[PDB]
Image (cartoon, grey):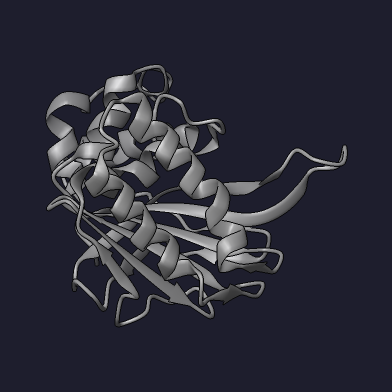
Amino acid sequence: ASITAITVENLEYPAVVTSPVTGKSYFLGGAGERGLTIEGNFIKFTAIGVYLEDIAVASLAAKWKGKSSEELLETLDFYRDIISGPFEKLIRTSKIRELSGPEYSRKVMENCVAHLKSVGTYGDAEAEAMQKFAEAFKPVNFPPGASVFYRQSPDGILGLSFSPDTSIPEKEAALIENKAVSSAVLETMIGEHAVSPDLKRCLAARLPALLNEGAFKIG
């Protein structure tokens, strides 16, 4: 049962969390830094952490038990099972430098629209969903330490939550009810065409120990 907390620029990601929204419990799959490769110096803007619902271990165990971290990292099918598995995923982006909602959401929505176009599932319903996605961010500003939570439900729903700190809000700001879009965000982070592989590495490193257990139980 060796899953640990991760800290990204003084922003702490606890090893386990329990949603006040769903009542489900999640474990930390990985965490890293994001920013811009601009002005010659790398400037950290956000931290990202990916949480998997506790039942994910039992679900992933069948196919991936006994595999090594090196092998998992090189296997696309592993991350597809994570992206599209029958369990909730919870992503937490924490700000290191202040960003408005539209400022932060710009690049995130670009990647999603790009992905949805790549795989040929960007129709009217998905464009509207991405519109509802944008609107959720417009009235919000993110000082340092403030967080956005993406709750990806396997039922094809994406819940957005904003917090002034790292704790999960009781209510969600919006519900994007679209299957293609619901998984789009996580795809841009650990999918095949994900630019930074730091989260892919983190997941590959942490899961094999859990998968040998056969299941994950908080407490």
Task: Give residue 188's quadrant in the image.
Answer: top left
Q: Which residue is drawn at 36% across and 53% down?
A: 130
The total number of labels drawn is: 0
Quarter of the figure with residue 11: bottom right
Q: Is the residue 31 above or below the residue 117 in the image? A: below
* Residue 205 in view of the camera: no
Q: Which of 25 and 186 is in front in this view?
A: 186
Q: Which of 194 and 10 is in front in this view?
A: 194
Q: In which quarter of the image is the C terminus?
A: bottom left
Q: Quadrant of residue 42?
A: top right
* Residue at the front extreme of this rendering: 124
Q: Where is residue 112 in the image (x, y as percent from the top left)?
A: 41, 41
On screen, residue 200 above or below 31: above
Residue at the location (68% across, 59% down)? 9
Res. 115 in view: yes
Residue 121 horizontal/vertical position (percent): 25, 33
Looking at the image, residue 15 lies above or below residue 145: above
Residue drawn at x 34%, y 42% as measured from the top left: 184
Q: Would you place residue 84 above or below residue 143 in this image?
A: above
Q: Which residue lies furthest to the right in this view?
A: 40
Q: Position of residue 5 (x, y in %)?
A: 48, 58
Tell me: 162 left or right of 33.
Answer: left
How far across and down, in percent of the image, does residue 29 sit? 38, 47
